[PDB]
Amino acid sequence: LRPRVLLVEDSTSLAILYKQYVKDEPYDIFHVETGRDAIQFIERSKPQLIILDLKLPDMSGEDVLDWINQNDIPTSVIIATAHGSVDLAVNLIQKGAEDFLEKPINADRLKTSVALHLKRAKLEDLVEGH
């Protein structure tokens, strides 16, 4: 019934701020610090949307996106990163990312993007389900 949002950030101080932003939003937000904990959350809990940082201490952010495409998880990925270029954004969106937010992110930049891509995914879900 209620949507799950995963937040994948090594900087776990910025994660609570991102939780503060979406505090009064109608979904649950969960936070992980490493790429392997993200993957394990995806395989178990199966969240509706991921807010994915590109810089992680164990692997790339791209590597998490690659895992979703390989195991066919129905999970929207928005990237949120520092030091992102035009070429990197393009190549990630092509790889199946649904947005690429650039740090620093506004309260309502993240809030809008999460809500929008949650909507598209929800609308496409409820036509193939009974």
Image: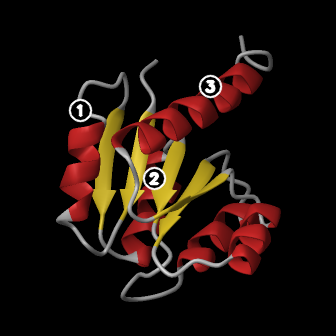
Measured as percent of width and height from the top left, residue 68 is found at: 66, 62
First reached walking from the N terminus: tag 1 or tag 3: 1
Q: Residue at x 30, y 71 (%)?
A: 33
User: Which quarter of the image is occupied by the C terminus?
Assistant: top right
Q: Residue at x 62, y 25 (%)?
A: 119
Q: Under tag 3, what secondary structure?
A: helix
Q: Residue at x 67, y 32 (%)?
A: 121
Measured as percent of width and height from the top left, residue 106 is found at: 38, 47
80 vs 50, nearest the viewer: 80
First reached walking from the N terminus: tag 2 or tag 3: 2
For residue 18, side relative to residue 7 (left or right):
left
Viewer-nearest of discs 2 and 3: 3
Q: Which residue is mark 2?
A: 44
Q: Amino acid at mark 2?
A: Arg
As drawn, the residue found furthest toward the bottom would be 58
Q: Under tag 1, what secondary structure?
A: loop
Q: Amino acid at mark 3?
A: Lys
Q: Residue at x 42, y 76 (%)?
A: 36
Q: Under tag 2, what secondary structure?
A: helix
Q: Which residue is mark 1?
A: 23
